[PDB]
Amino acid sequence: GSSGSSGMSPFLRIGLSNFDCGSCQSCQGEAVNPYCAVLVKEYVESENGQMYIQKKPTMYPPWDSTFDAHINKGRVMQIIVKGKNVDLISETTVELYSLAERCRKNNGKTEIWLELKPQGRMLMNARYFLEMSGPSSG
Image (cartoon, rainbow, N blue to C red; front, side, top):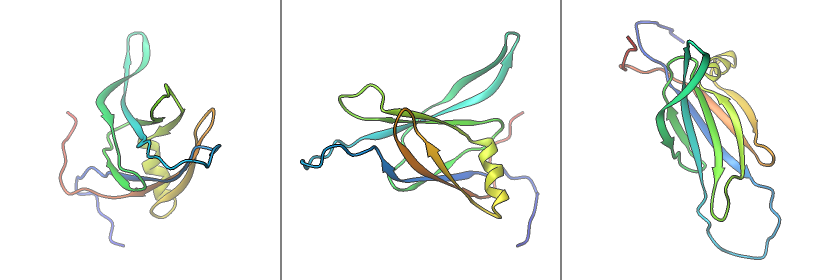
């Protein structure tokens, strides 16, 4: 209702749920305990051109839950599904900066369906939020 731009860094709250890895066999009852890796890079350009360095280490968000994300500028997010007896299940590209904008377009939060390749798919619900006090890039 009441907007305001005093000087706070807004953060994004993305939540992943209903992950489908294309079931093939339904004759077993074990827990692989898989986990997705959320890589966070930064936007930077050198004399060579444009590049992306992973300042933040690998992240491990919960399952079927929502996690908080830091917003700076041209930030990106990489979701890679990992597990056991496997080297790579799938991957997908996502924007941390642009996403923050898409949400607003939906008068709050926007619903996007990620497309993991070569196989796999999930729902990405990013919500808009505002902080009270955060760091400042000088």
